[PDB]
Amino acid sequence: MQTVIFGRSGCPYCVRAKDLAEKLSNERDDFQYQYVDIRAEGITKEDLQQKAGKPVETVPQIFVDQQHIGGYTDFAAWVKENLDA
Image (cartoon, rainbow, N blue to C red; front, side, top):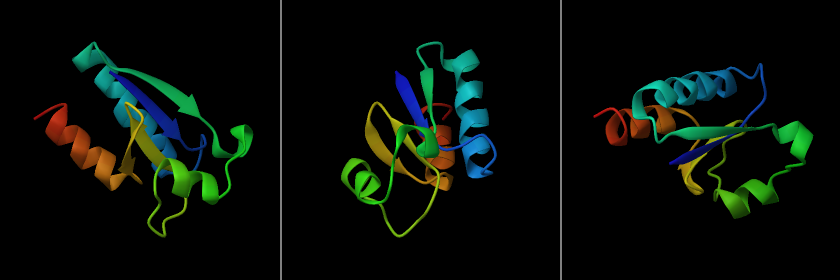
C-alpha cells in the first residue's frame, strides 16, 4: 500500500506521522510512504477541504491509498487497527 504525509519536518504531528509511517515500512513490507510538505507544494485550506474534507483542524494531516484518514490521532489509531491489529 502507499501512504502520503502532508506535514512539515518540525510541526510535531508531522514528525509523528512520519515516525509511524516510517516504522510500518519495516513491519508491513507492502507499505511505501511519500513525504509531502504543505508549505513547499502549495496547499491552503480549500485544497485540504477538497482532498481530505477537513474538519476545522490545521496541520498536518495523513492520507493512505489516497483516502483521507484525518489529522494524526486517527492515523495512529487507524494504523494500529488496520495495519498492526
